[PDB]
Image (cartoon, rainbow, N blue to C red):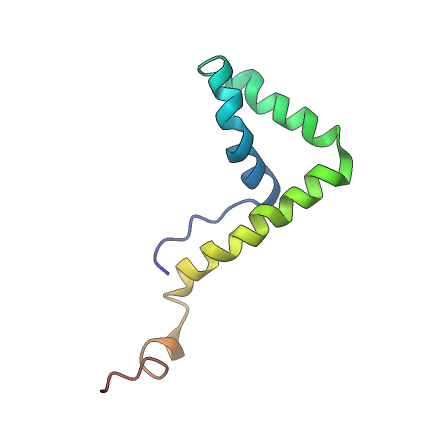
Length: 84
């Protein structure tokens, strides 16, 4: 990959997903923005929280490929085979 951003499953997919509109409403609502997201997150129980995990956890797979670049000893000489 290149650069591992490393999501956060729940707080990641969702926060970045909502915080944008929450921070927008008051142009820096973060204080109340990040909260509206936090409370509403637990207010939904396993429904939101958990499932939010996989959203960014499923996305976290995209980040894994980042560091992965360095964690591929047999993927940069043997699998790539520098030969035509």
